[PDB]
Structures are given as C-alpha cells and as structure tokens.
Image (cartoon, coloured by chain):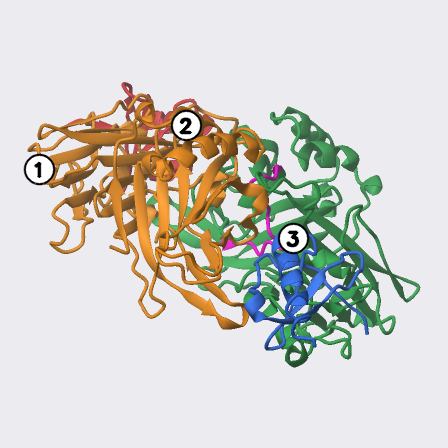
Chain colours: A blue, B green, C orange, D red
C-alpha cells in the first residue's frame, strides 16, 4: 500500500549515513532518505542541506556508475 | 455509591434560563457577581437543583472527613480526576462554578450550613470568598470564579472546610471545557475511618517512550502496519469494570511523532468502545489539541483547544454530535454495539489528548509524556 | 572547569551597542529576527563574544555527549538549573537568546559547524529553527525566541543535536529576568564516557509542610521566637567546601502563612552570605514575588515579578544596588565579610522565593512547595 | 514583646471554641480570637461572621 510522510525531520542527516533516496509527491511532497541501515527519514526537498545531499548523492552515484 | 461516572445530554432549551446561565455563570464575562448571581437567584428559587442538569459528565469520588479539632474543622480534600489537560498560559480563563452542599437535616440544627472551598495550586491558591458567592440557600452555596485554564488540571487540589460533618456534604466544581461541554468534579464526604474511594478514572500516556516513534523502525514489532490497519488495541477497561469495554490504539503515536513514511489512510482509530447494546446514558469523547496554523517561529505559542462529542442511542442505533473545528469524530464500529473515535493521521501531530467518558468509566488518553 | 557559576557587573554603556541588544534581542519586541539580527551582525562581526558581557550570571554544567550512530547525531541534553520561578500563566513572554558554539579548530574540518537546538516542555517543544536565527559564524549560531515566562523553568529540557563531537561545544540560553538582570544557562559538552557534572545549584522548599506555619503553635519548638530574633538558620553551602558559606532562615515561613499574631520586627533575614573578604566577584540576589495590591476575587489573575539586587566589593567594603520596588534588600552582616538579605515581615505573604548567586554557588530559595 | 497580624484567617472559627478575644490596631487592624485550647487567630473585623461571634460572646462579657 501507499505510504506518505506526515512529518519532516528537523535534524540534518549526514550524506555519510544515507544509502539511497526517493521523492514521493503527495499533499506533503518530500525527500525520503534511507539510512545505510534501513531507516527512512523524510526531509524538506526545499531545504538547502537536503538539496546538497540529493546532489552529492547523484554526483556520487554517477561517477560510481560506469 | 460515593463514587462513579455518569453522563446525560444537556439541552439548554429545557433549562430555566440556561441560555443565560451558560453565558453569565459558566463563561468568563462580567468580573462582578451581579449578573450571574441574578440569573441563579431567579432560577434556583424555583428549582433548587437546576444546575445539576448542566453537567454533561459527572465524576464523583468519596473522600473521608478529616478533622482539625483545634479549630473545630471538618475537612474534605481531593484530587479531582480532571478529564483533560487544562490548558496553556497563552490560553484565556475558564469560569468555574463551585458548589458546596449537603442533605437538608430533618430538625433545623442550631448551627447553620457553612463551607469554605479553595482550589489550591502550587504558586497561588484560588479561594472562593464572600466576594465570590453568586447564590446561597439553607444548605448550598454557589461560587463563581475565573481561573487561568492551565491551572485547572492535575496539581490543583480541591479543599472544602466545614465546621460540622453534615450528612451528604459534597463539593462540586462545574468545569466548562467548551461552550457546549461541562464536566463536574465532585467530592462526596465519607466516614473519617474510610479510605478515599476513587472513581474508575485513569490517565494513559499512549506515547510513553516518545523516542520510539521518531521513525518507523518498530512499526512491524509494535504491530502498527498496513496489515493490521494501524491498530494495536489494548484494554482500558479493567477486568471487573462496567460491561462496556474500552480500548485505545497506540499506533497514532507513530503518526504524531514519526518522520518516516507511514501507511496512507483516511482515518486512524484512536479508541473504540463495545457494549453499547446495553448502555443507557450517552457517551462523551473529548479531544485536546493545537491549531498550529498561522504560527510565528519567533513567538510560537499556540492555544490549546477542546471539543467534545456525544454519542447517543436512538432506536438501537448510536449517532454522533459534533463541534466545529473538532479533529475527531465518533462513528459506529463493526456493529451497533461498537463506536470508534476516528481522526485524520495528519491531525496527530497536534493532538494532545482524547478522553472517554461514559457510565462508570473515564479514560484520559494523552499523546505527550510518560506518566 | 566543565561546570560552575560566575558573575559580573553589566555596564551596557561599556558594551558595544548593549542598549540596542537588550531591547530588540533580549526583550519581547519585533516579532521578526530582522531587527536583532541587524544589531548582532554589526556588533558580533567585530567583537565575536560580545554577548558574553550581558550575562550577569552564568551557570554552566558539563554534560556527556550522547551518540546515535544510525543518524550520525551527537546530542547534549540537560535541565538547566533555572534560578527562579519562571512565571504565572498571566505573565507575558520573555525573549531568550539561544547560543550554540564550539572552539575554532586549528585546521579547517570536513563538515561545517551545525546544531539543532530545542527547548522542550511537557506540552510543547520550542524548536529554534532557521526562522529563529539572528546570527551565525563559522563556529557559532544564535537564535532568538519569545516564550511564555512560565514555560521557562524546571521542566524545560534543553536538547542540542550536533553531527560531530565539536571540541568546545556548548549551548547557552540567555534568560532575562528583569531589565537589569540576565541569567545564562550553559550546557558544556564533555566526554561521552564522563558523568554529568552539574553546577553547585540547589533549589530549596524552605516552607516544606506549609500547613505547619498556619498558626504559631510550633514557634517555640521550631526556634522561631523573639528570643531567637526569628532566626532558624541553616547552611545552604554543602560541607566546608566553597570558602563562602550561605545560610537560609526558615522562620520567614511563619510570617508568610501564619494567621496567628507573630512578633513585631521591622525586618527579617531571609538569608546571609559569609566570605565576602575573599570573594573577587559580585553577588546577586533575585526575589520573585506577587503584587500585593488587592485584585478581583472573581478573577484573581495575578502576575509574578522578579527583581535582582547586586552586592559589589568596593575596596573591601560591600554595597548594593537600589531595591526600589524590590521587597528584599542587601545589608552588611556582622563584618564586611558577611552580607544579609533583608525583608519586611509584612511582605512575606506575597514573596515566592529568593535566589542567591555568586562564584561557584547558586541557591534558589522557595517559600511555596513541599519538596 | 509586641505581636502583630500579617495575615487574617480565611476559615471561620466556631464561637463554641473562642475562649477570649481582643481587637488590635496598628499595622493591619484585626480581631484576635484566642481559642479554648490556647492558640490565637487573626480575623477581619469587616468580615460578616466575625461581628456575629463577638456579639454572641459579649452576652457573657
């Protein structure tokens, strides 16, 4: 079934702890980070630190992609 | 019985000037006893107990007489089981109506009826003085007073000092929680040699161990999944309790504190109640919450609101009544024998608590804390 | 020196734009960070630690780092030893400045300095968001926020989440209590393997079992007569440790709660302090009281007030600031080495508590409460 | 030495327990009921019940 974020984390998450991410878009669109051990934290897609991580990951999953 | 919980509908239309009593005696209006004391003088002369019909819920407890011989005092003191968080400092006040009374003896005694009631908190101690009376009679006095809402909650001890152990002596604090819901806390006096007799009224911190719900880590284990329908029910009603079983749901805590994706659902069930088939009096459900809309981070202080719902039996079918901004609703469950308290998942972060009030049972569920 | 207590005189005239800071930064004014952020960007960009001079009293405590590997968090949490009762629900708001800093590492680090700081009470958690920031630096951030005074007291937990165990990390909460008095609660981070190191700060229910002081039946026993000059002193300073010994008097309780006739004396000694001859910094004494001036018995809404006095050593001779509308005053003890807190017996009924603050010690004396 | 009232009781005293009595002016004008067991109690003279206790005690004084 569908899962939506109700609350967004209020603490930044180190890129050095994220594994992957997605961007579900409901009434409360958000970036769902998946920590290296399985936790799923929602974050503001508008937050600078989030954007920074989303980029850092795309730029780290690109070079590490052929 | 010296203790118990009871309910009743309250139609202000069928109440002597109730329309007025509500607005001038149970609402913080004129700062003088003039207005209210007028309305009650007129109405209580005809029917001495017209006030009893204003209590939607009445939670009474038996407290023993305590004597202070040196001063010849007969004292009864007790912790009223306030059904909900009183409020916040940023809130306004509530006009409460205190009432001391007792049976009218057969032979007129030599000493007349007198009672000093005080609602003492930590810092201050609100006293009901002569300047606070709004009505008197041979064996009953009624005091009016405005107390800041947050003062009216656990921590506020109710003490009434008498000079004689009048039979049937009792003190009642009529506490309006909303424009249409009034809870009456009652201390009924009992033998000095008797242990305090409390009503079946409990307080449950549904979300004890808040940290646990910061993420969906324990969802599977806690039993909160799409599979179970976000329902992990646990009994509120103790074993020998009334035939109406009440249950609470812990899962809402995830929807209130989690920053993890949770199953998308229209409503969560905060609690349910069976036994409606044999329940005669109504059922009240009160919610306490914040309206974080239009908040300023620099001065983020919101007011705590309260809405109370009522479920009643009509031709074997229970139906719900509602308040305006109420985040919760009552609807029939799996059968006519059950009712549930539904709320929207997105409302959980601002829901402070919900309380169940019905015959012989009162459960104050809170979503903050560990006690 | 992980923990401790320190004081200093505060000359706003000697402080770079101190007058503005304490009016748009430490006072509930513009509901926008803009003003205060303005003053602070100018002032602090020059003299970084300029805010430190506004702290009449600083009370720091060593608190162990608490890791959360899964989230890469390094948290420091602690309950500040608030000096006096925050306030009543009737009071206004107090604007606080929350600072988070750390030492400037000699070599540029990987990550940048970061810290989320929340002030959480039972019902609400005031998070200091980006919308609250009024200043930032490579290794310092200052937030600002208005909170109802009553929330700022024991019960408020201070929580600081970081991402690295920044050497020198510490969260400070500058809390004004009056126009001339600002108390700063500092949470200094210490080894995760260390034990909490709080400061020598005690809270004391001077009038425990207040029912005892309702009459003068226990004056002879309690040693509170005229034979004793109404003085039942008790050491506040533990052991023969800190060279300055402070003492409290329990007799004031009688003058606060007793409805019996008590001795007549122009003054009472609420407390005293010895060791002024070796004390190299000023002593502070804050009284918390309710305004006498009779209110409306129907709506007893009364505000809580705070006033701080300052004792300074001028050439070995100690003098204090004016106690204009302050119920208490500081005078010289038997020697220049001793100092006393004096009060009129008449003002005891409305006195809530007095706090003594000096080098290494802080004593919060409360006249209400049983523990 | 001398004794004063800093506070006036809020509870009533049963007249069937006040051995003596005495009015005192100065700081706060009050009434000082002494109880049959000793103990003294400061009350308000303006307080309605008070005057009732004095007079019904004056029929014996």
- CA distance separating discs 2 and 3: 48 Å
Q: Earlier in the sequence, mark 2 or mark 1?
A: 1
Residue B352 horizontal side relative to residue B225, left or right: left
Task: Point out the frontmost of discs 1 and 3.
Answer: 3
Question: What residue is pinned by disc 1?
Answer: C277
Q: Measuring 55% from the left and 59% from the top, which residue is drawn there?
A: B62
How many labels, in total?
3
Nearer-the-camera pick, C32 or B252: C32
What residue is drawn where x is 47% and y is 54%?
C113
**Along the line of sight, which residue is nearer the eye, C131 or B85?**
C131
Q: Which residue is mark 3?
A: A47
Q: Chief secondary structure of the magenta span?
A: loop
Q: Is residue B329 magenta?
A: no
Q: Which residues are magenta?
A: B78-93
C-alpha span from label 1 to label 3: 56 Å
User: Mark 3 — on which chain does it sit?
Assistant: A
Residue at the extreme left: C335
Question: Which type of secondary structure does the marked residue at label 3 adopt?
Answer: loop
Q: For numbered disc 2, what is the local secondary structure?
A: loop
Q: Is residue C12 visible?
A: yes
Residue that lies at the very extreme toward the right in this rendered image? B315
Circle 2 Cα neighbour tier, 10 Å, few/some/many (<14 / 14–19 / ≥20): few
Q: CA distance from mark 2 to mark 1?
A: 36 Å
| Residue of label 2 | C291
Placement of B139 over or under C324, stated as above or below = below
Residue B90 belongs to the span the image colors magenta? yes
Placement of C22 over or under B140, stated as above or below: above
Q: Position of residue B251 (x, y in %)?
A: 68, 70
As drawn, the residue found furthest toward the top would be D26
């Amino acid at each position: 079934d569908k899962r939506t974020c109700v609350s967004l984390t209020t603490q930044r998450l180190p890129v050095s702890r994220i594994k992957t991410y997605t961007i579900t878009e409901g009434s409360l669109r958000a970036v769902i980070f998946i920590t290296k051990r399985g936790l799923k934290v929602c974050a503001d897609p508008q937050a600078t630190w989030v954007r920074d991580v989303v980029r850092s990951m795309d730029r780290k999953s690109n070079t590490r992609n052929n | 019985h010296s203790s118990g919980v009871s309910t009743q509908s309250v139609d202000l239309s069928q109440i002597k000037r109730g329309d007025e009593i509500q607005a001038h005696c149970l609402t913080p209006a004129e700062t003088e006893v003039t207005e209210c004391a007028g309305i009650l003088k007129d109405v209580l002369s005809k029917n001495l107990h017209e006030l009893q019909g204003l209590c939607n819920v009445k939670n009474k407890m038996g407290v023993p007489w305590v004597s202070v011989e040196e001063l010849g005092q007969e004292i009864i003191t007790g912790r009223l089981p306030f059904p909900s968080v009183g409020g916040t400092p940023v809130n306004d006040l509530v006009r409460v109506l205190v009432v001391a009374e007792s049976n009218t003896p057969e032979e007129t005694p030599e000493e007349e009826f007198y009672a000093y009631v005080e609602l003492q908190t930590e810092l201050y101690t609100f006293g009901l003085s002569d300047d606070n009376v709004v009505f008197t009679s041979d064996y009953m006095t009624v005091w009016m007073i405005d107390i800041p809402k947050s003062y009216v909650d656990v921590g506020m001890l109710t003490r009434a000092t008498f000079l004689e152990q009048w039979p049937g002596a009792k003190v009642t604090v009529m506490i309006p929680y909303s424009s249409t819901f009034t809870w009456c806390g009652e201390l009924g006096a009992i033998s000095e040699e008797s242990a305090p007799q409390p009503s079946l009224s409990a307080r449950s911190p549904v979300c004890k161990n808040s940290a646990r719900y910061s993420t969906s880590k324990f969802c599977e284990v806690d039993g909160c999944t799409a599979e179970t329908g976000m329902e992990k029910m646990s009994l509120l009603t103790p074993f020998g309790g009334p035939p109406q079983q009440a249950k609470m749901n812990t899962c809402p805590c995830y929807y209130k504190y989690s920053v993890s994706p949770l199953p998308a659902m229209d409503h969560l069930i905060l609690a349910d109640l069976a036994g409606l088939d044999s329940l005669t009096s109504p059922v009240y459900v009160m919610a306490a919450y914040f309206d974080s809309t239009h908040e300023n981070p620099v001065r983020p202080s919101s007011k705590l609101y309260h809405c109370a719902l009522q479920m009643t039996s009509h031709d074997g079918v229970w139906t719900s009544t509602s308040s305006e901004q109420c985040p919760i609703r009552l609807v029939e469950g799996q059968s006519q024998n059950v009712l549930q308290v539904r709320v929207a998942p997105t409302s959980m972060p601002n829901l402070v608590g919900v309380s169940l009030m019905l015959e012989g049972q009162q459960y104050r569920l809170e979503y903050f804390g560990d006690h």
